[PDB]
Length: 346
Image (cartoon, rainbow, N blue to C red; front, side, top):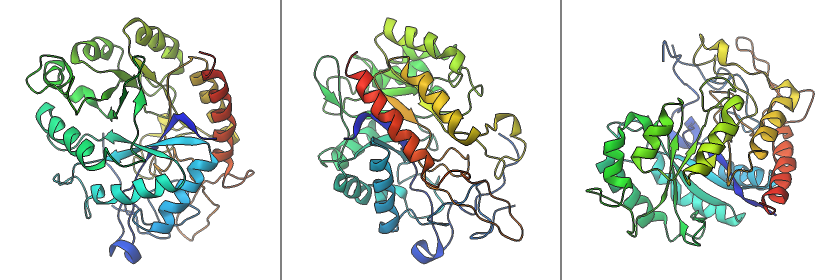
């Protein structure tokens, strides 16, 4: 059975010459601070996908991804989303793949929710527009995710990455009752999940009107929110203030193909043990949802997607030996079933 309460962060930003006319994302630039890879032999990842330097628009890729997520008993993909009108994307807008993704998710009884990226000049005004757009265009699709609240009401969910860039007073225009562009008590109401990075964000989130928090980062120690030391405190905080706590767990982290300096935030997978430690840490908070970073953020080495050994003449790749390419899907299934069993007792 699928765990309806387990979400994974999904990316549809990959392109290749066969499907897109060029590489997209695999030819990721090497960043200089907070010179591009040459696919297919040299991609912007420390690992190599079983599907190769694949295209996110290739229907066989999307099919395989939905099968893998069902095999992991993940019920919901949280789709990285940019509005089409921004100049944030190097191809054709990724919003034009959302219908295919919803249809493919539905084949396997998966749901799709939205991870709103930090698009150019995102604010309260264009967030109202984009929330309305997502619910109007996608909200009637049978694979469209809603979360049933304490009061019985089922609402769309929006994860807001780097929410803190926008000041609380501006969020309150959208997220509080009497705000100038309120979605509250409207057909466009939702559960808005803030990214909690720093401990001081707790108060900002309360002033903003958010409905919950998530932590995203797969590195235990990168941020206050991402640190297992703080998850009991964040759960206490969320329970006290009627917020949905969504801890984010990853299987490892390595982004040095794109951020060569960032060795401090590398986390060895310990042949699956890092992931199992983080899953244990999340489950014992008795959270309402758990998120997994990531299905396929290959740049940052957080993926649970199948990876394979690969040798080339110029690039070195990590892999999942001495285990199989599907290790992380198998570990996810084990912990998904434990979470389903324990959550039914809360």
